[PDB]
Image (cartoon, helix red, strand yellow):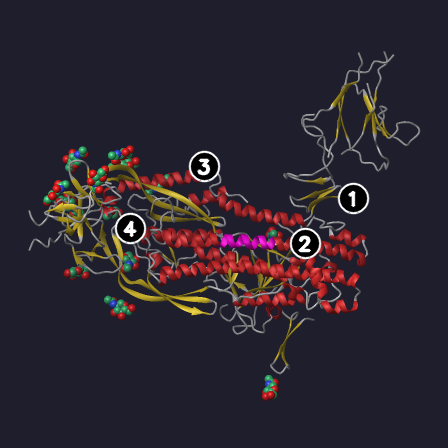
Amino acid sequence: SFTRGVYYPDKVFRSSVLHSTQDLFLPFFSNVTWFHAIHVDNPVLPFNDGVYFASTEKSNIIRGWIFGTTLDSKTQSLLIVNNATNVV
Amino acid sequence: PLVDLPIGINITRFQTLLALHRSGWTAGAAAYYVGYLQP
Amino acid sequence: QQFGRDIADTTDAVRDPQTLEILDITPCSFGGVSVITPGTNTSNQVAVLYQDVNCTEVGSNVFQTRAGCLIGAEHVNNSYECDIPIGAGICAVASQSIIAYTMSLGAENSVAYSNNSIAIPTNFTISVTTEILPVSMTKTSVDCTMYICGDSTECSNLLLQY
Amino acid sequence: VVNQNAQALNTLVKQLSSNFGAISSVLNDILSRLDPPEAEVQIDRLITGRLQSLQTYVTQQLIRAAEIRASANLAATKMSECVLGQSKRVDFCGKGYHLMSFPQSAPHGVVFLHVTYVPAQEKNFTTAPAICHDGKAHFPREGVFVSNGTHWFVTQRNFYEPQIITTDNTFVSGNCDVVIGIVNNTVYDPLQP
Amino acid sequence: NNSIAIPTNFTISVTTEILPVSMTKTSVDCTMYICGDSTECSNLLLQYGSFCTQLNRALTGIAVEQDKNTQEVFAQVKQIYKTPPIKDFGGFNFSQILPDPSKPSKRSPIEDLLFNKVTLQKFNGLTVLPPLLTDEMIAQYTSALLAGTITSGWTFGAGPALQIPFPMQMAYRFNGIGVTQNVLYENQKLIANQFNSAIGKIQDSLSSTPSALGKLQDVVNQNAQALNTLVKQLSSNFGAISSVLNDILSRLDPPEAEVQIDRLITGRLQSLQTYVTQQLIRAAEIRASANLAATKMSECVLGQSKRVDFCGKGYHLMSFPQSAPHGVVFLHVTYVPAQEKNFTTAPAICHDGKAHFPREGVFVSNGTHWFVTQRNFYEPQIITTDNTFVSGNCDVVIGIVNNTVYDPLQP
Amino acid sequence: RTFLLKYNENGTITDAVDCALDPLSETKCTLKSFTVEKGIYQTSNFRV
Ligand SMILES: *[C@@H]1O[C@H](CO)[C@@H](O)[C@H](O)[C@H]1NC(C)=O
Ligand SMILES: *[C@@H]1O[C@H](CO)[C@@H](O)[C@H](O)[C@H]1NC(C)=O
Ligand SMILES: *[C@@H]1O[C@H](CO)[C@@H](O)[C@H](O)[C@H]1NC(C)=O
Ligand SMILES: *[C@@H]1O[C@H](CO)[C@@H](O)[C@H](O)[C@H]1NC(C)=O
Ligand SMILES: *[C@@H]1O[C@H](CO)[C@@H](O)[C@H](O)[C@H]1NC(C)=O
Ligand SMILES: *[C@@H]1O[C@H](CO)[C@@H](O)[C@H](O)[C@H]1NC(C)=O
Ligand SMILES: *[C@@H]1O[C@H](CO)[C@@H](O)[C@H](O)[C@H]1NC(C)=O
Ligand SMILES: *[C@@H]1O[C@H](CO)[C@@H](O)[C@H](O)[C@H]1NC(C)=O
Ligand SMILES: *[C@@H]1O[C@H](CO)[C@@H](O)[C@H](O)[C@H]1NC(C)=O
Ligand SMILES: *[C@@H]1O[C@H](CO)[C@@H](O)[C@H](O)[C@H]1NC(C)=O
Ligand SMILES: *[C@@H]1O[C@H](CO)[C@@H](O)[C@H](O)[C@H]1NC(C)=O
Ligand SMILES: *[C@@H]1O[C@H](CO)[C@@H](O)[C@H](O)[C@H]1NC(C)=O
Ligand SMILES: *[C@@H]1O[C@H](CO)[C@@H](O)[C@H](O)[C@H]1NC(C)=O
């Protein structure tokens, strides 16, 4: 992971100050599971506390993400998609 | 932060959506990385 | 970002809605109020020093110093030995009125230094100086059980938990 | 010190009149009209406030006692080095050269009357580090060389008493060619007559 | 039992002793800090007694004590002494410690460097009263003390400032440390060169070594950290539903909100009391340091102190005071033996059956002849009746050697 | 109003000071003395 996964903890603005906060963060230099879209691939992963998603691509293969408990018509599910018009 | 939405429902599973390139599907050469947040 | 915070947990800036601009929030002026008085015997006339605050906002004689502003004491330019401590090098009664002046550190004198000249005393004065030093204080004793719990058992039982 | 102790005691007694969130400051008065289940919590609040006030008074007394101990240690050192003896340390026993001091008792304290010597009626003199005589450099054994404008004299630094330059109040070291600012004068040898 | 080491040479060393004299005169308002701009918390706070008056008075007492500390350490001179416009000090150079006219603050390069080295806001209920003596005024006091010690030696401390040439004052100080004044006069150029070199080196050391002013930086940091923690404790719930008073007052009815407001009020009162206690202890430590600094100014600057290591390592010659933010830096000029030589030594000289002991200094033997020299400098002199006194005979003193005591009267 | 009342040995109120009348009266009230000595005295807090 190197030094990635840091996000602004809040909408609070701070200038030239060091701030210490305890939130859900991706640990530095941690092992991150990486997958290649091409097969010579989108497995279903658990969500747990949070997910840091990194994308290295040029043709925008990764268009969206799906979140939920059962991932089927049985239960309510969250769906973010990019249909080349807008994020829905 | 780019989106904040009051969804209200638990999330226990996550799945990414990929753009399948027609040749029979051959996905583009890309890397997607998943890192789990910890307290 | 919607609002900014200082190094401490206090809000320094906000993003104003209806205009999308940044407004700095300064704690509005406040300060202690000190009273310069020469003493009831000397005069009933007194001056008011508003501490660490500008006084363009709340007026007969106003003098602004780093310690705030003095009202009712006139500022003179000639210095004097400090009579009342005000602060920031300023001190304050003369001519039946309260005056404010920069402190005078003492009588400025230059010793006539020369590489071949010495000053030698032809006489002496035997002086006596009084130095007062406290050596002890009142030996006060306070009993907790009587002091916090007066002549009652139940307060003593509650005290025993402490 | 007396006022601070009295003021601390006055605050400590005045703190009893405070409620500390109780229905009344008087312990028995709230106790007389309240049942033990709710009187207990009211008494607990009063005890917490009063105990905190007593702890604060004890802490303030401890800091004041440490300051008084520091003052007393300084007073004991002054009694030893100014009254029991003579101190060469400047301003420890009063302005000026310290001659002696007298202790006086006072309520919760001691007053030292420091008897000190202060130079006065000083006069200008032309001074010289050394005097050249017969090719030899003479330096004052005790005191300094001073000229009133016609003659040179040796005098103690702290009092002007002119004395003729001689071989017993001056010592010879080196030659006149090494001393900077040396002057020429005659050293009266007592053996010469 | 018969060997001695005499310093044939010496050196002048300048050492800095940095002592805090005062802390920032902070002042808290108990009512505003604990209960912010609300009547409801104020009414409950009034039920806790005179705690806010006691805390405010304690902080006022520390602030007055800080002013008294600065006045005691620096204002030890009845008059303001001015250095002569011509720096004819017999080769001694004080440019690094005398105030510089070109600078827009009458401060010497050394104190200006000290101010530049140490590096340091509006809060709610918290204010910093300015010091009674300004930095410029404190620097003027330091300059006056420095001019007085440079021109009148230690006389200005005792009473009227009596002018004395600086080489002659240095000779008196050398006599004060047990070295005859002729040693300085024979070595005035060497001593002046050493003094200037040490004065340059000490400014270089202050400019090059960090943490030299760390004692002064530490008290400023401790005061700032205590203030920062006290402000940070405003955001602590202390068991209340929310830290901010307005939210708990707005969302809860007063009959139930009173217990939450009480939890916040007691927590803030306890925090302020802890801060005041920490400040009181820190002020006591600062006062002890200021008392030490005042004693050091009285005995090392206003006078020459024979107390060992009280005014710097080595035999103390003099001290130069320098102002610093919330502190004083003492430049102790001291005499240190440099080159040491062995000498055969006898407690007494046996001449014609009589035992002679040195009036001052010790007997030395370089290996062929015996001489009498001062202990702190090797200046051998022939044994005479004027520098040695006769006591008893040679059959009582143990370990003595025979020699000729030249009587000056005899030839 | 807050009032500082001077009771004589017989309990008669012989004098009074109104703490809100003028800054000198406030100084007398804060020191709890009808007569104040020379010096600075902090009596109140000005808050806008
Ligand atoms: C105080 O008022 C004067 C005059 O308007 C102004 O120049 C100065 O900047 C003000 N200072 C502060 C700290 O508000
Ligand atoms: C020294 O001063 C005293 C007064 O302090 C005076 O009586 C005495 O005559 C003076 N002596 C000389 C020698 O001037
Ligand atoms: C010495 O002479 C100088 C100048 O002539 C003068 O300023 C000083 O007051 C004199 N001091 C004494 C003690 O006579
Ligand atoms: C200096 O002192 C000597 C002492 O004999 C005296 O003869 C002479 O007149 C004095 N001169 C002055 C100017 O006082
Ligand atoms: C003092 O300085 C002057 C020049 O200003 C010089 O003529 C004189 O010799 C010097 N005297 C001593 C004792 O250094
Ligand atoms: C002292 O005398 C020597 C020769 O004996 C001479 O060279 C020197 O200039 C004289 N110095 C003074 C101060 O008169
Ligand atoms: C004494 O030491 C200094 C500095 O080390 C040197 O400059 C000087 O020449 C020495 N003098 C003697 C007499 O050795
Ligand atoms: C003292 O040293 C400084 C170093 O910059 C120099 O400028 C100055 O001329 C020196 N003073 C004397 C009297 O030599
Ligand atoms: C002589 O002095 C040197 C140090 O300078 C020391 O090492 C040696 O032991 C001494 N010898 C004697 C006999 O004193
Ligand atoms: C010791 O001192 C004598 C007399 O000053 C001298 O002649 C001799 O050369 C010296 N000897 C040594 C070993 O230094
Ligand atoms: C020192 O001790 C030696 C024995 O090691 C002895 O011969 C000599 O007499 C003693 N000298 C003195 C001065 O005590
Ligand atoms: C010194 O002389 C005495 C007789 O005057 C003699 O007994 C003794 O041995 C001599 N000592 C030395 C060290 O020469
Ligand atoms: C107080 O009452 C007594 C009666 O014993 C009377 O003598 C006195 O004058 C009264 N004093 C005052 C001040 O009222």
Q: Do the residues bearing badges 4 and 1 touch, measured as CB atoms within 8 Å?
A: no
Q: Is residue A17 magenta?
A: no
Overall secondary structure of the magenta stretch?
Answer: helix
Horizontally, residue C128 falls left or right of residue E395, namely right
| Residue depth check, mark 1 versus mark 3: number of the one nearer the observer | 3
Q: Circle 3 — which element?
A: helix
Per the model, the C-alpha gap separating discs 4 and 1 is 80 Å
Q: Residues within 10 Å of mark 4 (few under 14, many from 20)?
A: some
- Identify the residue under disc 1: C18
- Identify the residue under disc 4: E176
Q: Is residue E278 magenta?
A: yes
CB of residue at label 4: within 8 Å of ligand 7?
no
Per the model, the C-alpha gap separating discs 2 and 1 is 36 Å
Q: Do the residues bearing badges 2 and 1 touch, measured as CB atoms within 8 Å?
A: no
The image quadrant that residue E32 belongs to is bottom right
Horizontally, residue A7 falls left or right of residue E332, namely right
Numbered badge on residue E208 = 3
On what subunit does the disc labeled 3 rest? E
Say yes or no: labels 3 and 2 on the same chain.
yes
Say whether disc 3 or disc 4 marks the residue closer to the N-terminus.
4
- Identify the residue under disc 2: E268
Specify the amino acid type for callout 3. Answer: Ser
Report the magenta residues as a range. E275-287
Q: Do the residues bearing badges 3 and 4 touch, measured as CB atoms within 8 Å?
A: no
Q: Residue at x 23, y 42 (%)?
A: E186
Q: Is residue A27 above or below residue C75?
A: above
Say yes or no: labels 1 and 3 on the same chain.
no
Say yes or no: labels 2 and 4 on the same chain.
yes
On what subunit does the disc labeled 2 rest? E
Residue E36 at least partly seen:
no
Numbered badge on residue F17 = none
